[PDB]
Amino acid sequence: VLSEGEWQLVLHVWAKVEADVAGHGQDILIRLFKSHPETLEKFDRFKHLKTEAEMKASEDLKKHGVTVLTALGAILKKKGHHEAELKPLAQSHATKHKIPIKYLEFISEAIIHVLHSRHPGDFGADAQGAMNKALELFRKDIAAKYKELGYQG
Ligand code: HEM
Ligand SMILES: [Xe]
Ligand SMILES: [Xe]
Ligand SMILES: [Xe]
Ligand SMILES: [Xe]
Ligand SMILES: [Xe]
Ligand SMILES: [Zn+2]
Ligand SMILES: [Zn+2]
Image 1 (spheres, protein in one colour):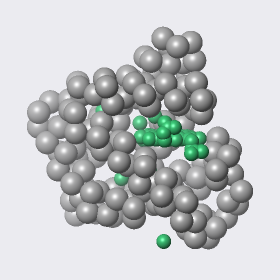
Image 2 (cartoon, rainbow, N blue to C red):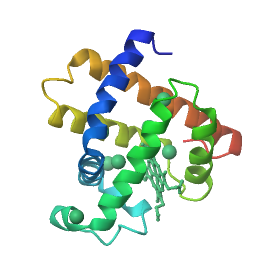
Image 3 (cartoon, protein in one colour):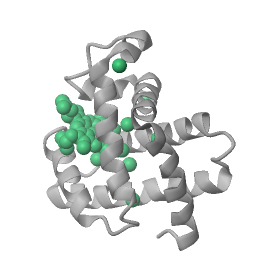
Image 4 (cartoon, rainbow, N blue to C red):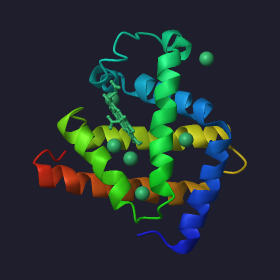
């Protein structure tokens, strides 16, 4: 697990995301889709977007970015005691959206990239390491639920 000092790094950085949830959310989803266009295919809602300019122009995509970061923020704020918040998410992503664990790894990389881009002064290697650990813990617990339900990977 994360040490107290590492959770402090994560939660203090997260406060910076909360100062502009829509901007960070938009940037993270665009970075995911550009870096890994195969992830687009999983969203019937977005698969029509073919270019980066189209992604930037979509109000619906910006709305979903808020949904994603609001859910992730609720989880991080539980400092690992996130069973009630994580369960519904693991269920829907395994059984309904059918999202492989690898794509959760890809979105974790996009989050780190955007935090670095937006906060070059604030988000040094120690915070980056701590954020990586927090997202790993998130993935580990989702993966366990996937395995339970017979999806895993
Ligand atoms: C940071 C990790 C992620 C969080 C916190 C997250 C959160 C959510 C939330 C809260 C919803 C709406 C409720 C629901 O259906 O459960 C949702 C919908 C969805 N998510 Fe995720 N998600 C994450 C990663 C991903 C990834 C990597 C993909 C695909 C590559 C994905 C695919 C979807 C799809 C297809 C929907 C349904 C969208 C719609 O048609 O309305 N999610 N996500
Ligand atoms: Xe996001
Ligand atoms: Xe998820
Ligand atoms: Xe994640
Ligand atoms: Xe972010
Ligand atoms: Xe987490
Ligand atoms: Zn890829
Ligand atoms: Zn707008």
